[PDB]
Image (cartoon, rainbow, N blue to C red):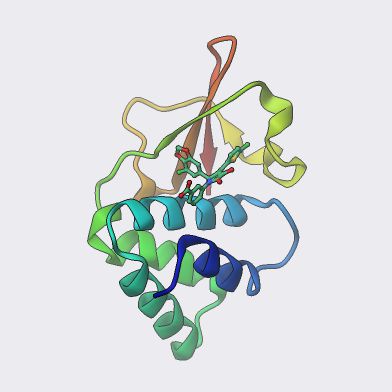
Length: 123
Ligand SMILES: O=C(O)c1cccc(N2C(=O)C(O)=C(C(=O)c3ccc(Cl)s3)[C@@H]2c2cc(Cl)c3c(c2)OCO3)c1
C-alpha cells in the first residue's frame, strides 16, 4: 500500500517552489492521513481533482474539505525550536493563532516554539 512518504513525494511532484505553505499542508495531510489509515482515499481524491482539471493547490485544499478526517478539525501542533526551523517560503504565511483555528478554513498547522511562542500557518 501507499505510504505517507510515498504520498508526500507524489504530492510534492506536483507543487512549484520548495518549503512553501502547500508543502507543509502536504506534510499535515500525510501525517493525519497516516494516523487515520486514510492515505488511500486522500490519494484518490487528490488524483480525481487533478483529473477534473484543478490545480494541485486546489486539489490539496479540496482534500481538507472533502475527506472527513479534516472536516471541522483543528490543526495539529508541531513542536519546534524557533521560527528559523520553519522553511523560508513559509515565513510570510505565519500568523498569530486565532481562537478556533480549523484546517478546512486554511489553518495548516500550529508551530509551538520552545520559548512559548505559537504561530499558525495560514493558507
Ligand atoms: O512520523 C510520521 O509518520 C510522519 C508522517 C508524515 C509527516 C511527518 N512529519 C515529519 O517527519 C516532519 O518533519 C513533519 C513536519 O511537518 C515538520 C517538522 C518540523 C517542521 Cl518546521 S515541519 C511531519 C509532521 C507533520 C505533523 Cl502534522 C506532525 C508532526 C510531524 O508531528 C506532530 O504533528 C511524520
